[PDB]
Image (cartoon, rainbow over the protein chains, first blue to last red):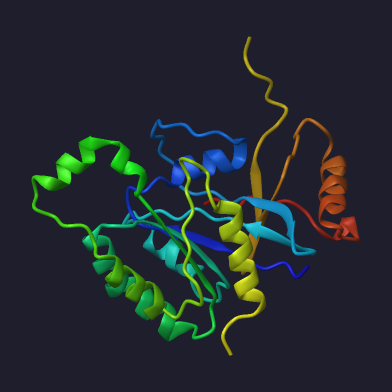
Length: 181
Length: 56
């Protein structure tokens, strides 16, 4: 029942705009449309508790770093979407995200979901990444990364197929209800 | 046939707090806007709040 603030962040070129369009209108456009920032406040109740998701859009542009990092302090929860198998993405995550959230707030619940995994159905990207001599991230290292970021249980949901999203939000709420000591 | 414009999206922020959304129609008098804002946010003393622009 206790309403809390929320911030959603992510990597570059991952699909925030389609996520917001789907959230506000229940659709899935493949067209790319620029968007600066957004906030959605929706009233959904899970496990008998009425909690409002104060959604927030964040942009990776260099210009608005002052605006973006202003609200990062005293934020209570994150929803992050990232390309699952991009070594530069994991490198940037280790360099930027995890150390700061660990040093600033030792007790900030974090919900993490990976993206860019249905592209196996599209051979174009497979051929694109084959010519550059890139190998997929080993599952053992992925699980080690999931368990080493102070996360109770890491889970993933589909945006294109719309699979697990409600389950992911429910498990995040359950984890926040009974987090680590 | 242009689409109706009676529905718009606007987030009203707070200093140090995260936004909440409402539909505001400017044609109606500001008294109606204040009443609807207070009804939506369950805030009493409608005469102790007003509207200002957070742009430049």
